[PDB]
Length: 130
Length: 296
Image (cartoon, rainbow over all chains, first blue to last red):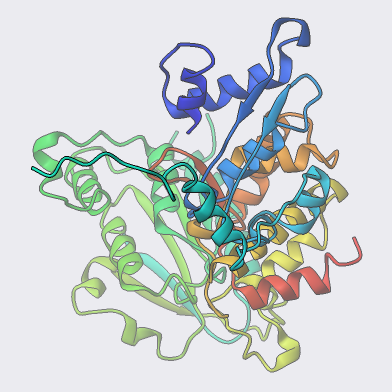
């Protein structure tokens, strides 16, 4: 992940560790007059934290710094995944927003299916017999 | 070219130290004429002894020649081969004592293993270093083979003084009739933290709490290892947020004391990170957190 992010913001091509320090310095010490806001979309987050909580902790902590301009959006399966990984006090310090997506019902699903077929349903077609 | 072995009932620590340090070394130094012969005290009652560190310090003191590629063999041990090379080298130098080593408990909970005995037996063939040792167990001679007794070249002496032995009985909990898992070594950690500064205790508390969290999330009686450690950068970020350490220099300066006493280890995984970890058990860690660090 690290290098990819760096490769998408600087054009350089470094290893993962050097990318980690590069991103840390960039988000911490570069003045706000010479940057640009970045919207990361960390996806399938449960597949990154499988040996240690390093990636999640770094990505969530980079939003704490004042000089940074980061807006992280992370999606996952389980709700209370960070609590099971980081700890209650660190999560309380970070202070993110939480959203839960409930399943569909038998009305919304029918509405989706009907919306996806509007022009075609009950229409007229010219058909060649041969 | 003999090797003394003192046996009896009581404590032989003060006697051995007073004999080796205050009498033998100055006499040898004066007899070979300037500086005194260095002595390598080797605690035996400590369950956390490791022969790799002992051989590292032996190498530092004696500065032996390195090992060529043709002598390393196919995945061969790099300690016994170097000891044999030193033995072959030291068979021509003039006969002069250059090092004196004291083994306090030759049959302790961790020094009685076969590999350590083999290393010590090979190290005693060299005539240029002097051995002094003592034993406490009563089936001690069963520990030595018919070949180890040949190159140890022991001479047996008896000294009984009914000494209290108040220092050897520090790594075990006497309050529980001495059934406190002697090979663990968790009592020494409590004794050390009993007399440490305020800043170090908070850092150890933070490390223990994080390691316990990781152990609980990952897994009982399982011991903690590198898999349940804390990354050095993450630990620095955590401790810097509680006004414990300011930069990495202070953290690495205050971690050396804990590393030396075999109470914390630092090692690198396959991905190149640095992981610090405590080689204790979950129950022992909880007891340490509850009995001595709960009140600060």
